[PDB]
Image: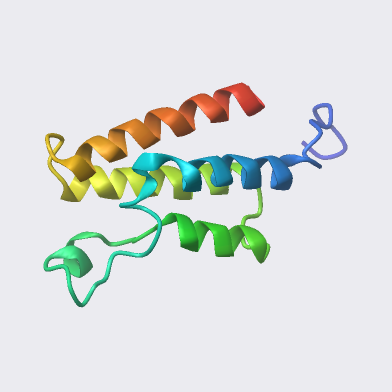
Length: 115
């Protein structure tokens, strides 16, 4: 509360560390469904159904331009990518499986880096 603060957790490396995690996600072999925004002209249903599209390139640009106020808003956008994928794709599809694999990969790096 006012003039009463928990001890200051060092957040000075968060930007660099989120960038590293993002590089690792970008270079994973199963990243291909997620590298670029879904083409809303060419994929029926996407625009109407997925209210907040997100992809790794968009996260990379947001990261690079100071549009994440803290590491939790970064994690929210990464998870959004996988949540969108599960919304639109069957579990038993190449894309659906890619999304589960990537979410797993991300959540481990997240825990190991920060928790």
